[PDB]
Image 1 (cartoon, rainbow, N blue to C red):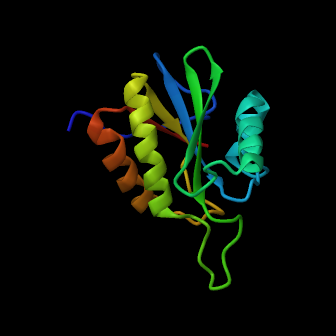
Image 2 (image 1 turned 90 degrees about the vertical axis):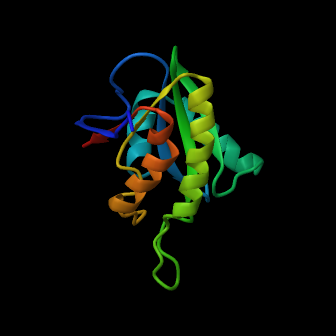
Length: 157
């Protein structure tokens, strides 16, 4: 019980603190990169977007629950986590967010972060158009990261 999610004001593309850092965000499964946090990423680094777009074309494990890790600076990675289905709600009004997919992604982030002695930095992942409910998303993050003593910072903006 040593760790707790930290919430601060700011921009997850400008992560706080020291050591190796992984910026985690939720991507869709159709290769779309044009709305929300991805725009903040691409302002600062071309690599996450380009890696993701190449991944979409490769169709090599481009599936819900999969994660691509890209280096953007000395000691800084971005995790492109495929955690939402499509961009818009489906025919029965189900929002794109897939909580099970996000959890699977976070299991892979946990292993990566442990191996690299890293901390996690994120926006309020899933909130907004993906239709995620923070009270649920937060619980998944606590279970998959915080309980293993991986620091997590959520950036409000």
